[PDB]
Image (cartoon, rainbow, N blue to C red):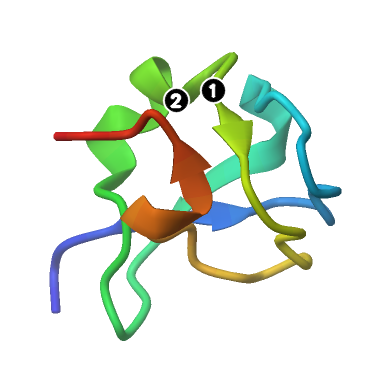
Amino acid sequence: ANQASVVANQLIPISTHLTLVMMRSEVVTPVGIPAEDIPRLVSMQVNRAVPLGTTLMPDMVKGYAA
């Protein structure tokens, strides 16, 4: 487990466009969106509410493909 994922740094309400302060990098299980993609995620919209400390998964971000 050395791969870090994107984890919500605050509750992200449904349909919010992500900003940098909302995203942190953490080694969590299961693995979500790779923490290196945090750059690309800015301005993309989440399609559900992501509570504080939840791993951001590919299927929670609208338009995400990588």
User: Which disc, if any, is residue 41?
Assistant: 2
Residue at 29% across, 31% down: 37
Residue at 33% across, 53% down: 58
Vertical placement of residue 30 versus 24, above or below:
below
Q: Nearer the viewer, residue 63 or 53?
A: 63
Q: Is mark 1 in CB contact (under 8 Å) with mark 2?
A: yes
Other residues around mark 1 within 10 Å, as few (<14) / some (14–19) / many (≥20): some
| Residue at the outermost bottom position | 29
Q: Which mark is nearer the camera, 1 or 2?
A: 1
Q: Nearer the viewer, residue 48 or 11?
A: 48
> Residue 18 vs residue 41: left or right?
right
Which residue type carries mark 2?
A: Leu
Residue 10 percent across, percent down from the top left: 81, 52
User: Which disc, if any, is residue 44?
Assistant: 1
Q: Secondary structure at mark 2?
A: helix
Residue 52 percent across, percent down from the top left: 77, 65
Other residues around mark 2 within 10 Å, as few (<14) / some (14–19) / many (≥20): many
- Residue 19 sits in quarter: top right
In the rendered view of the protein, which quadrant contains the N terminus? Answer: bottom left
Residue at 84% across, 56% down: 11
- Residue 64 sits in quarter: top left
User: Which disc, if any, is residue 10?
Assistant: none
Residue 56 percent across, percent down from the top left: 48, 57
Which residue type carries mark 1?
A: Met
